[PDB]
Image (cartoon, rainbow, N blue to C red; front, top):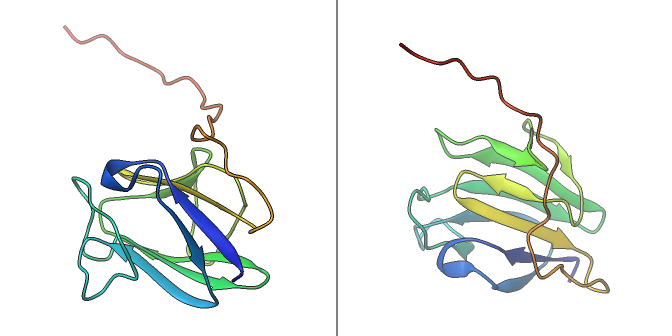
Length: 120
């Protein structure tokens, strides 16, 4: 198989799965999801990827979430980077080639500091 995925959230924490070529839907509904995710806030179809030998492409995701890669919002059609930290709301995951190892801890990202404004 082409790639493997590791989950770092929810009841899937620590799970690892090898992926062949084609469409991969992740979500809480087993009728619609290739990878069943059990966590609060996971949609019936939460995230849809297209996998081939060359890489992993982001296709679709649940309303109310924004897919991010090391904190940066991604758009439909983006090619995702192996071993970067992927998030989509509650879901945290990464992927890599079968000949490489996953980090034990989810990849930390440098996020810019938020502005704040005191209320009164």
